[PDB]
Amino acid sequence: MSVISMKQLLEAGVHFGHQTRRWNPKMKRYIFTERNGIYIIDLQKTVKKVEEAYNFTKNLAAEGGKILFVGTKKQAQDSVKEEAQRSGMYYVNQRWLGGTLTNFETIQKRIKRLKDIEKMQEN
RNA sequence: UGGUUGUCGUCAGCUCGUGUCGUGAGAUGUUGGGUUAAGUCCCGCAACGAGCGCAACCCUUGAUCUUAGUUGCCAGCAUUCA
Image 1 (cartoon, rainbow, N blue to C red):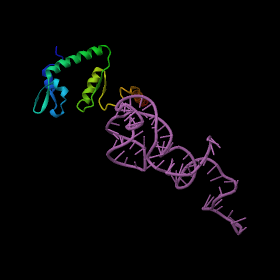
Image 2 (image 1 turned 180 degrees about the vertical axis):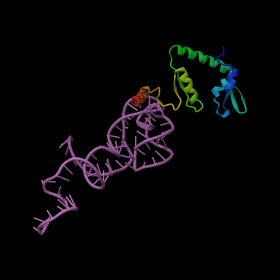
Image 3 (image 1 turned 90 degrees about the horizontal axis):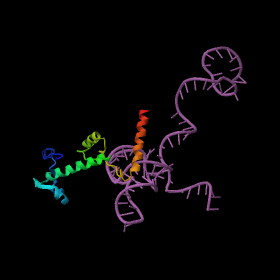
Image 4 (image 1 turned 135 degrees about the vertical axis):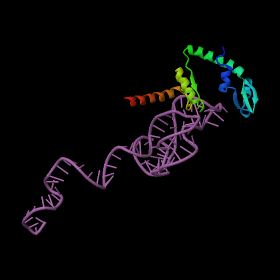
């Protein structure tokens, strides 16, 4: 089964891309046509690719994989947090701090710090 | 040479851990928008923190309460050259 129907994708506006002047030639594989100066994403391949992504995530999640939802874009900040909270996963919705993954030890110390201040406030 | 001192200069600066960028020396952080006496503080930001500086902690002066009332003080009380 298609994890998402083309009707839902159309209502969600998945077919809307960016302006022709901002197009990436590598994205040509996923573009269906151009209309009114805006590129339209090929929803037929979109359905197939979304189905693969959902299955991959489910396999990875069943192996205990931790998925981090990242979106600082103003339109996405709220959605990322709400959906991550529902799934019990982590999110970065305000600003990605450089070194969050490559310098994980340094971030953990700051994470530890926050928890200490919380305990001082509660106690 | 040790120890000590002058000097830039009581100027607001000088660095480091990890990360990232650069073939490399390096850079970033520490730049930028406001603000400050100040790298002082806020915000932004491939940076995230830390340290020596800055400020504060110390001394003195300016107000006042408590304790203490002599060798200090004399208002109310008499007396003295005081």
